């Protein structure tokens, strides 16, 4: 055991970050709730 095991748990977020951001990004029309929710403060 060295780095053969810890592949998925490395790759996950590396991709989940892109994937999730895609999911949100190409659905701003929906996630708009949060967008507005974040505009009211800050």
Image (spheres, rainbow, N blue to C red):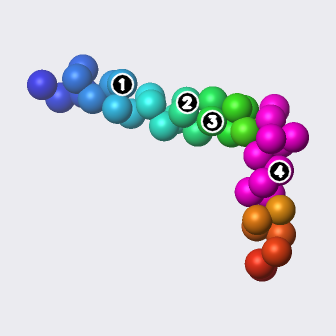
> Residue 27 lies in magenta, yes or no?
yes
Q: Which residue is drawn at 78% across and 79% down?
A: 42
Residue assigned mark 2: 15
Residue assigned mark 1: 8
Q: Residue at x 34, y 25 (%)?
A: 7
**Which is nearer the N-term, disc 1 or disc 3?**
1
**Which is nearer the N-term, disc 4 or disc 2?**
2
Q: Where is residue 19 in the image (x, y as percent from the top left)?
A: 63, 30
**Which is nearer the N-term, disc 2 or disc 3?**
2
Q: Position of residue 17 (x, y in %)?
A: 58, 39
Q: Label 2, label 3: how many angstroms apart (C-alpha)?
A: 8 Å
Q: Give the range drawn in magenta.
A: 26-35
Q: Main secondary structure of the magenta part?
A: helix
* Depicted 4 relative to depicted 22: above or below: above
Residue assigned mark 4: 32
Q: Label 1, label 2: how many angstroms apart (C-alpha)?
A: 10 Å
Q: Label 1, label 3: how many angstroms apart (C-alpha)?
A: 17 Å
SS at circle 4: helix
> Residue 28 lies in magenta, yes or no?
yes
Q: Label 4, label 3: how many angstroms apart (C-alpha)?
A: 15 Å
* Depicted 39 relative to depicted 19: above or below: below
CB of mark 1 within 8 Å of CB of mark 2?
Answer: no
């Amino acid at each position: 055991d060295a780095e053969f095991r810890h592949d998925s748990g490395y790759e996950v977020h590396h991709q989940k970050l892109v994937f999730f951001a895609e999911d949100v990004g190409s659905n701003k029309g929906a996630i708009i709730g949060l967008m507005v929710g974040g505009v009211v403060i800050a």
